[PDB]
Image (cartoon, grey):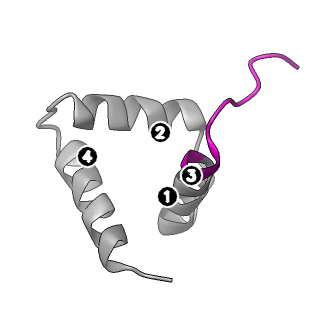
């Protein structure tokens, strides 16, 4: 066991939701790495795209 996920309720939804977007199961660690770099001001294509994904999400209401 151990190394259990400690993501918040909102974060859990975000990770599962990102998976839904890629329709493929991804790890939480990877998600943290992606946001970490993006939020850290990364220029990588995945970073700007990630920020956009948040923007698209903002557009997508219940």
In front: mark 2 or mark 4? Answer: 2
Q: Residue furthest top?
A: 2
Q: Classify residue 8 by image quadrant.
A: top right
Q: Is residue 61 magenta?
A: no
Q: Which mark is residue 31?
A: 2
Mark 2 crowdedness (10 Å alpha carbons): few <14, some 14-19, many ≥20: some
Give the alpha-carbon distance from disc 2 to disc 1, as whole Å: 9 Å
Give the alpha-carbon distance from disc 2 to disc 4, as whole Å: 11 Å
Q: Which residue is mark 1?
A: 18
Tell me if 59 is positioned left or right of 5 in this view. left
Tell me the element at label 3.
helix
Q: Position of residue 41 (x, y in %)?
A: 14, 32
Q: Which residues are magenta?
A: 1-11
In front: mark 3 or mark 1? Answer: 3
Residue positioned 49% across, 58% down in the render = 18
Comes first in the chain, label 2 or label 1? 1
60 versus 27 height, above or below:
below
Q: Residue furthest right?
A: 1
Q: Position of residue 6 (x, y in %)?
A: 67, 29
In front: mark 3 or mark 4? Answer: 3
Q: Which mark is residue 49?
A: none
Mark 4 crowdedness (10 Å alpha carbons): few <14, some 14-19, many ≥20: some
Give the alpha-carbon distance from disc 3 to disc 2, as whole Å: 14 Å
Tell me the element at label 1.
helix
Tag 2–tag 1 contact (CB < 8 Å): yes
Comes first in the chain, label 3 or label 1? 3
Q: Which residue is mark 3?
A: 10
Tell me if 42 is positioned left or right of 58 in this view. left
Comes first in the chain, label 2 or label 4? 2
49 versus 62 height, above or below:
above
Q: Which residue is mark 4?
A: 46
């Amino acid at each position: 066991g151990a190394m259990a996920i400690a993501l918040r309720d909102d974060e859990y939804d975000e990770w599962q939701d990102i998976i839904r977007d890629w329709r493929k199961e991804m790890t939480v660690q990877q998600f943290l790495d992606l946001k970490e770099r993006a939020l850290s001001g990364a220029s990588d294509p995945d970073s700007q795209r990630y920020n956009a994904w948040l923007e698209l999400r903002a557009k997508r209401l219940s």
